[PDB]
Structure formats: structure tokens, C-alpha cells
Amino acid sequence: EESQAFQRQLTALIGYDVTDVSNVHDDELEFTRRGLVTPRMAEVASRDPKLYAMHPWVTSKPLPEYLWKKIANNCIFIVIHSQTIKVSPDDTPGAILQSFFTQDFVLRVCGRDEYLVGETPIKNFQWVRHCLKNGEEIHVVLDTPPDPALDEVRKECDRKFRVKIRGIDIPVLLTVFVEANIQHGQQVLCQRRTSPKPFTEEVLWNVWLEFSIKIKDLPKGALLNLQIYCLLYYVNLLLIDHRFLLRRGEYVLHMWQISGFNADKLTSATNPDKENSMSISILLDNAEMPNQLRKQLEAIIATDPLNPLTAEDKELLWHFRYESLKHPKAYPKLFSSVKWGQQEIVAKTYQLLARREVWDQSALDVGLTMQLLDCNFSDENVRAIAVQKLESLEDDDVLHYLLQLVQAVKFEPYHDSALARFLLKRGLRNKRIGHFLFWFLRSEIAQSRHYQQRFAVILEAYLRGCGTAMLHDFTQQVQVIEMLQKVTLDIKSLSAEKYDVSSQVISQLKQKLENLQNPESFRVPYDPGLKAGALAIEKCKVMASKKKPLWLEFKCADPTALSNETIGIIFKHGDDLRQDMLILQILRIMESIWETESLDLCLLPYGCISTGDKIGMIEIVKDATTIAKIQQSTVFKDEVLNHWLKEKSPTEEKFQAAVERFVYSCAGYCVATFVLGIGDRHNDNIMITETGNLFHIDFGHIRVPFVLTPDFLFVMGTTSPHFQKFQDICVKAYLALRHHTNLLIILFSMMLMTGMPTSKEDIEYIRDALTVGKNEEDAKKYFLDQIEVCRDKGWTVQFNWFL
Ligand SMILES: Nc1cc(C(F)(F)F)c(-c2cc(N3CCOCC3)nc(N3CC(CO)(CCl)C3)n2)cn1
């Protein structure tokens, strides 16, 4: 029927068909679809239709000190469309509009699908804080509120565990053996192997693998990890399914192949390529502490998330678990001290979680919550108390952590989890969260066979509750990016390689962009407030980068938009943009951290969205150019950069503002990059705006600690009065990140596992970079040594890349 045409629209939006059962050996996925219906409807029938349509973007956080100093009269001016209006920072939208008349009209931002509404001071609106920080005037049009009817939704034993290894099969390709692990949170409970047989296209064993664990000692979420060594292939089977039933019967599991640790290795999904992939065939038929110990316990609790716990430490934590329960910071280490392979201990663990008044009353610590949601915890009861703390996150904070909460779904043992349901709720409650939730989920569905099925089921559940209006937006957005990505590919084939630009390329590009325009208006995926109209064909070009990316520019479809600037987007194939997304988001989290301490390092975390395999889109920051390109124009010469700034800034005052913007923006990327270990970059990959705002680009796949070349130093003048500022802002910013050391360490390690090509040694860099277990005095001295290395080295590393 027509209801089945609705499901075909969902499939096109998703990029995957969730009704397909071609790759399932149980009904867990469908069971989850049905299970997600409840949380969907509960959030739909509970959200306010009015605020849902206007979707006010608001924060409950305080107004930073560096923004108060920009309003030195306690008078915020709002230009309504037109007379300017004197307003107090604590003036509510209603008190402003009623003061405007002296009835149901609403204030909407010019050139944006954004609204300033609700019981909140204008001081607490994100669009207002943006205008203030960037010294812009708040322009708004008195418009009629969007029809809430547009958001309407289409209503809907003591025996040891045994495994029978029959054999492996592959029509492709030493000696191989089968290793079967019983795993829980990457903790190998017991391990058994087969005998090494000749590696042929068919290898049968017909052997029972005896494990040391009993059947009723198997914890929920425990994985049967089956691996082949010559390690070339792996595959997993949940031993207890979504119905708490011990898994039994025959299985033919198509395994994933290894390339020559990370989240993919954990998935319960089987390889969908049954034609080429290796197969496996199996059979299942079944007082209080003394002073000295308390100090040792507290010392253990105080260490970082990456500090390994010894057997003694674990035994200590467990025996004094009720003492450890009083410290929320002890929870990650405590639950790592649990013998999950023992039913009795798991029981005591649950009774311990029964009364958790301290944990329930503690202030929300995201860094501590994330640690409970990573690969080290499979127990759903432990993970639930994590998602519990997330519930107190305001929408502004959900957006901060959305990308890596979505990635964290990869660490969930089952498809239907508290973490999934949480994202679903918060996505249906806020259109901005829902919008980015769509693109984050869709990003993984398109280039991850390991998790596309789970993410698809989740995306379908969101799409059925977001409302008919947003379904229309997503469809337009999807249709446009599909057209543009086609043009991106065809143009890449024509240029080939070793040719900067051809006459025939500029011809075909402007030809296809003309043909393609005959998609009236689409929402900008990386900036959902902005809508894009007709292409500015004359501005469109191929940038002549290594991959020949498209430089496209559009017109804003909003006539109320004051300016006439175009919306720029770069389409690129060849780079894995999922890595740039993760880095950029961490940059935003660093900005957020710095805001807590009234800092502003002027980072420019541009918009970036992965849409497919090595393909996606990148926001174009206006009036920006490469620092290396600035050297090629006049020429190695260090005087150049300051010369370029004077040229672009007409007034002498605007120039000093650029140098102020520079010393700030410079310091921000110095600290951020070193902490993340991406500071040693080529001059080409660093850009600057005409207003002196420095920023890095292209974070995919990445000797000096970072980049502070003499050309940058010349802009500072060198010791100088503003270099003293630079050395000052860095230590302030650096020591500020160390105050959130645990949060940064967990996000970093998660970024490596869920988005990078990843062993223990890789993560430990950020720990050293953050000077773990060091005094603030010594740490400040550490970072300054790093600054001096950029001085002593000069262009030594800079010149090297030229080969
Ligand atoms: N993974 C990637 C890929 C790209 C690339 F566009 F494909 F090259 C970029 C990037 C962004 C950018 N930005 C992003 C911020 O807004 C301005 C454009 N400018 C450039 N340039 C290459 C250049 C060399 O001179 C061509 Cl004109 C400038 N490159 C970043 N990350």
C-alpha cells in the first residue's frame, strides 16, 4: 500500500533497508525496531509542538567574562525588521516584543531558520552570544511562528560451556588454527584453540572445544569470539541473546578479514559479502579500613583512566568495594576489578549498584560517564548508570558530545541499549540534535558494514518521529549531496593526475553545474540554520588539489538575509573525513573547556561532514588563505606574513586587531594540536583569514612539537610585548586542558578506536602531552620548552616536506 511507499522513502533517506533479513541469524534487529517504537512515541507525544518547531538554541551556562567586557553599558541592541532597540542582557524575548509594541508574532533571525523565543534571557541564546563574540549586530525579522501542524507525525546448569568447531570455508587464497575466546568487555574469560591444520579452501575439525567456565557463570553481553590464525579473520556471537536465552544450534558465520584494538573487532554483525568472505561453522547445544590501606586505595582511585590496575589493586578495590562506592571517580576502576566470569560476584556487583546514593547525587562528570560507555564495559547495568547521568545534560551539551556518543553505540553489546534510546529521545526532543543525529548515523551507515545494520535501525526509529517537515528537509539534502557527489567523481576521473588544471575541466564543470541546475533550496548539512539556493556557477571551480576537489558556492535562499555573501562548500573524494569530523568536534570541546575559565582562543572548527566512503563536504571559511601560499606570492621569508596582514586590513586599527586575533588564534592551535599530537604540520595545511584568525585544516592521517615558525614569530616581533602574551595565553590554555585530563584522555582513546586505522602505545601520547602526574608549575615549564623548540628548529622541518 501507500504505507509501504513510506518505508521506501525511509530506505532512500537511510541508505540501507532495515526490513531486509538477508544477513541475520536471529531476530535481534527486528526485535529492536519493535522495541524502539515505545520510546519514540513517548517522546513525540510529550514534546511541546511550539518550541519544537521554533527549536530555540539555548544554553543555561553563564555569560563568559570575555563577552561581558563587550557590553560595557548593560545595553544590548536588537535591530527588528526597521528601528534599533535598547535591551537588557536579562530581557526575555516576550518582554522585548511586548516592549516593542508598547501579539503572537515571533522574532526570527535574518537569513536564518533560527528563532529567539522561550522563557530565556537574550543573553542565553547561542545566536546572540555569537553576534557579541564576533562583534555583529543582532538582526531579526518580526515573523509569524511556524505552524506546529507541519511537525505532525505519521502515526504508527553446572556443565562447562562447549563449542563445536566443524570447520572453515573460503573460495579464496601456511597453516591455520581456530581460536575461540569467551570475551566480556575485551576481558578474555577463557580461551581454547584447535589443532593447526593445512590452510585449504575447506578445513573440517569436528571438534568440541571445552571451556573452563560453567554455563550459569556466563554473563549477559558475553561474546564468543572466533578467530583464525595463520590473525586474518574474526567473527563474534553473543552467547546470551536479547531474550536472555542461552544461544544454541547450528551457525554458519561469514567472517571479517584483517588488513595489514578498535571497535570493528567487537561487532556482532556477520560479513554480508557471502560470495568472497571466509566462513565458519559451529554447533551449540547446552568494620572499616586501616589508615595505610585507605591511602593505597585513594592513590589507586586518583590515577588516570589509562593507568593499568594490577591484581593487587583489583583485589583491594573489590574487598573494599563499599568504601570505593563512595567515590564516583572510583567506579570505572572498581567495575574493572569485577570477575564477570563468576555468577556470584556479578550478583554482589548488582546488589552493590542497588544502593548508589553517592553516584546518584554526584554532579554530572562527562569524562567519568564516557569511561563507563567505552569498550571496557559490557555489563548493561553498569552502562545504564552512565546513561543515567547523561539524562541531566542540557541540549547544548548533548550537541557538544553527540558525535562521540553516537560512536559509543559501537561499544554496546546489544542493538537495543540505554545509550541508543537516550540518543533517540534527545534527538526527537530537539530538531538541531535530530538533524546532526541523522548525519552522524548516516555517515556510519554508508561506510561501515560492521555497524550499518544497528545504526540503520536507530536512524529509522528517529525518522519515524522527527515529523513530516524534517523528513522533507532530509530528502532535499540527500538528493542534493547525491547530485553533487556524482559531479565530484566524474570531474576527478577527467583530470587524472599530474595536471594542475585543464581547459576541458573548467568547461565540463560549469557545464554540469548548468545542466544540474535544471533542487530549489536545501538545508546546509553542517549548518542547519542556513538554507542554500541557486548555485553561483561563475564562482564554482576545481581547486587543483591532489584529489581535484570541487569549490562550490551557492546563494542564500532566505530573502530576509541582509548580506549578499555566498555559501561555500568543498566536495572532496579521496580523504577519510570521519577523522576530520572527530578532530573538529574535539576542538569544539576544547573551546567549551576554555570557556569555563573565561578563555577564548578563537579556534575556527569549520563545518565538516562525512557522507560516504572517502567522500564528504567541508565548510568554506570566507576570505581565508594558506600561510604557505602567502609565502609563494612574495617569494622562507619570515617578514611576509605581517606584510600580507597590513595589505588586507585598510585601517591601522584593524591591523592591530588582526595581530590580536592572530596571537590568540595561534596559541589555541598550538596547544590543541600538541595535546592531540597533530601539531607538526606542513605550512600548506595552515590557513589564516584576512582578520588574522589562524587555523589548521585537513586532519586526516596525522621533528617539532607543533608549528610556531619565525614567519609567525615575526608577526609577534622577535622577546616582545605580544610574544609575552603568546607564551602567557598558551600556559593558561594548556593548564586549563589539564584540569579536564580524564575527559580528554577518554575522548582521545575513543576517537582512536572508533575512527582510526590502534594499539595501547598510540593512546599514551596524550597522557604525556598533558603531563599526567605533574605539578602545574612543572607543566607550565614543560610547554614553554616545546615553544623554544619551534624557535631553535626554524624552518628545518618546514623545508623538509618540500621533497
Ligand atoms: N580532508 C581535507 C581536505 C581538504 C581539501 F579541500 F580537499 F583539500 C581540506 C581543505 C579545506 C580548505 N578550507 C577549509 C576552511 O575554509 C576555507 C577552505 N582549504 C583547503 N585548501 C587546499 C588549497 C591549497 O591552497 C586549495 Cl586552494 C586550500 N583544503 C581540508 N581537509
Image: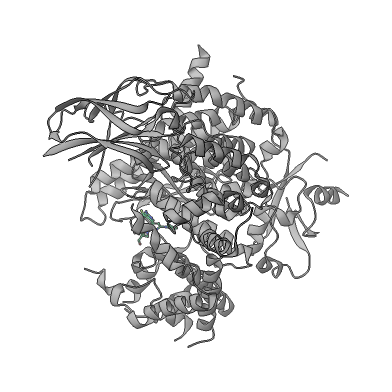
Residue 214: x and y, percent? 39, 30
Seen in the picture, residue 499 relative to 52 is either above or below; the reply is below
Front residue (pair 7, 96): 7
Residue 324 in view here: yes
Residue for point 44% across, 75% down: 644
Q: Is residue 85 left or right of residue 554?
A: right
Front residue (pair 3, 415): 415
Which residue sits furthest top? 1
Residue for point 64% across, 47% down: 393
Residue for point 33% across, 67% down: 682
| Quadrant of image for the C terminus | bottom left
Front residue (pair 409, 106): 409
Residue 689 in view here: no
Q: Quadrant of ligand 1?
A: bottom left
Residue 204: x and y, percent? 17, 25
Seen in the picture, residue 234 relative to 594 is either above or below; the reply is above
Q: Is residue 525 left or right of residue 486?
A: right
Residue 386: x and y, percent? 57, 44
Seen in the picture, residue 242 relative to 98 is either above or below; the reply is above
Report the coloring of the rendering. one colour
Residue 328: x and y, percent? 60, 52
Seen in the picture, residue 279 relative to 353 is either above or below; the reply is above
| Count of marks, rendered view | 0
Could you say which quadrant of the image residue 157 lies in?
Answer: top left
Which residue sits furthest front? 287
Could you say which quadrant of the image residue 263 lies in?
Answer: top left
Front residue (pair 736, 655): 736
Which residue sits furthest right? 102
Could you say which quadrant of the image residue 713 lies in?
Answer: bottom left
